[PDB]
Image: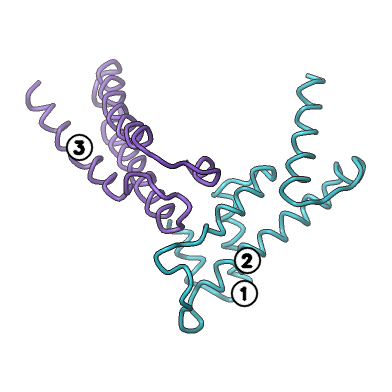
Amino acid sequence: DECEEMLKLFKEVASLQENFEVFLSFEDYSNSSLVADLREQHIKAHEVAQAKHKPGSTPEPIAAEVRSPSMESKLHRQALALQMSKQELEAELTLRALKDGNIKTALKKCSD
Amino acid sequence: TECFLAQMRAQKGELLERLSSARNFSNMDDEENYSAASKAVRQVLHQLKRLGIVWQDVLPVNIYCKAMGTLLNTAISEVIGKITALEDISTEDGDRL
């Protein structure tokens, strides 16, 4: 159990270092405040990565027959360390869209 | 027996069709190829969930489990064949697969 816990701690540290280039001490690492802050920061980042992709203007001649990697996949690469599944991501997005006054996007996600 | 398997082949003739959007599981780097692949996989599990709910407490335990295993075998052996017939799998593909 000691080795499994220590392995989990170093796995989290290495995943956070490689996917984010964030380097601190273990006292700053184990503090849940930074974990929650980085979780909400990349929740907001995922909000924008799709919000810009709802067309507010005419599309650009980019990703034409050669489509760019999805932002959701990069967010999931980041969140594999954060242990956030798709259900929790959709739950958080529903509340965040509800706070923005967007009703349809929350109802559609609830229905799905 | 023959009446029951007539329902099985009708159900299989749905699952493979729901996998028609899998696009041979190629070019996972594209966002559309990832979305259209998730669309097939969600619906394949959803069909079996509802079918199992329908057949719940109707068939005996042995035959229900055997029929479910038989349907899931066809569901999984198609994805396995699609993956083993691929040619290019990059680092991004190895994560989304």
Residue A104 on image: x %, y %? 47, 71
In 3D space, how far apart are the residues under numbered discs 2 and 3 (Cα atoms)?
Answer: 40 Å
Residue at 66%, 59% (x, y): give it.
A43
Report the residue marked by disc 2: A96
Left or right: where A63 falls relative to B51: right
- For the residues labelled 2 and 1, say whether their Cβ atoms are less than 8 Å apart: yes
Chain that appears cyan = A
Chain that appears purple = B
Work out whether B49 lies above or below A62: above
In 3D space, how far apart are the residues under numbered discs 2 and 1 (Cα atoms)?
Answer: 6 Å
Left or right: where A40 falls relative to B79: right
The chain carrying label 2 is A
Report the residue marked by disc 1: A100
Disc 2 secondary structure class: helix
Disc 3 secondary structure class: helix
Work out whether B63 lies above or below A31: above
Residue B87 on image: x %, y %? 39, 39
The chain carrying label 1 is A
Report the residue marked by disc 3: B11
Residue B91 on image: x %, y %? 55, 43
Q: How is the image coloured?
A: by chain
Disc 1 secondary structure class: loop
